[PDB]
Image (cartoon, coloured by chain):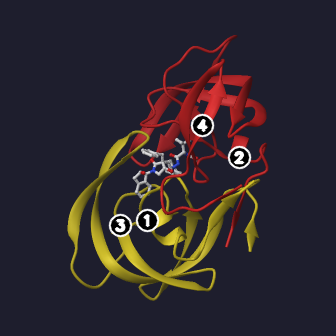
Chain colours: A red, B yellow
Amino acid sequence: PQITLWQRPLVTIKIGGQLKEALLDTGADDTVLEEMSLPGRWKPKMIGGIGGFIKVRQYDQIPIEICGHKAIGTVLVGPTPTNVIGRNLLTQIGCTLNF
Amino acid sequence: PQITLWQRPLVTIKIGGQLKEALLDTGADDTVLEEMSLPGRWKPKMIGGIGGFIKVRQYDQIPIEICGHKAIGTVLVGPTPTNVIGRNLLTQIGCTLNF
Ligand SMILES: COC(=O)N[C@H](C(=O)NN(CC[C@@]1(Cc2ccccc2)C(=O)N([C@H]2c3ccccc3C[C@H]2O)C[C@H]1O)Cc1ccc(-c2ccncc2)cc1)C(C)(C)C
């Protein structure tokens, strides 16, 4: 589909069998979601944003559906102000910017 | 043009007679640039992202050019770790997400 930007590009995603709302964010290298439980072991990662850095848990090869599109990749979990889908997953669903 | 998301979507913008590199950021409501001088009035604003909030100066009705596309809108100036082009200007150049 084609999504205009007059409003926030918020979409429904499915992870761990649950539906959540997330923002398609081209300004993000990675995907970071609010606190939640994910399987397996995680690795640490420090990610920097507009206001500084935060600590997050990194889970790899996690199945996640975005707007119905299937993806399997790295998901960071931590104290983010909102769920954001970064380029690591936007590329998996074939997303591009056009104008 | 069609911008790939395999890499960060960086573009050249022309503002205040200067040329700067900025990130096309669909997750950003506003446009924020590192410290620079801009003409006209302004008012303080606090914007929050990953890591917390930062204080910026809000300048309205600022002419800007992105990839040859002219537009006008609000530009925030402050200690942002990187230049970001937000939805308020992405809409004016007719930028959309497609997949
Ligand atoms: C390489 O780093 C990244 O890709 N970081 C991502 C990130 O923050 N991206 N933001 C952008 C992330 C988001 C997330 C958000 C969405 C809704 C509500 C609250 C927050 C954000 O915080 N945004 C803020 C923003 C930006 C411009 C103008 C106004 C505002 C207010 C707020 O919306 C836009 C979103 O895209 C742009 C950015 C890029 C590099 C560095 C850096 C930091 C340190 N050194 C150099 C550059 C700092 C910031 C993560 C989500 C993974 C943290």
Q: Amino acid at mark 2?
A: Leu
Q: Nearer the viewer, mark 2 or mark 1?
A: 2
Mark 1, ligand 1, within 8 Å: the answer is: yes
Q: Nearer the viewer, mark 4 or mark 2?
A: 4
Q: Residues within 10 Å of mark 4 (few under 14, many from 20)?
A: few
Q: Amino acid at mark 1?
A: Thr
Does the residue at mark 1 contact the one at mark 4 (Cβ under 8 Å)?
A: no
Q: CA distance from mark 4 to mark 2?
A: 14 Å
**Residue marked by disc 2:** A90
Q: Nearer the viewer, mark 1 or mark 4?
A: 4
The answer to whether marks 4 and 2 sit on the same chain is yes
- Tag 1, which secondary structure? loop
User: Which badge, 1 or 3, comes first in the chain's sequence?
Assistant: 1
Residue B76: which disc? Answer: 3
Q: Chain of mark 2?
A: A
Q: Position of residue B88 (x, y in %)?
A: 45, 67
**Residue marked by disc 4:** A12
**Residue marked by disc 1:** B31
Measuring 43% from the left and 57% from the top, which residue is drawn there? Answer: B29
Q: Quadrant of the N terminus of chain B?
A: bottom right
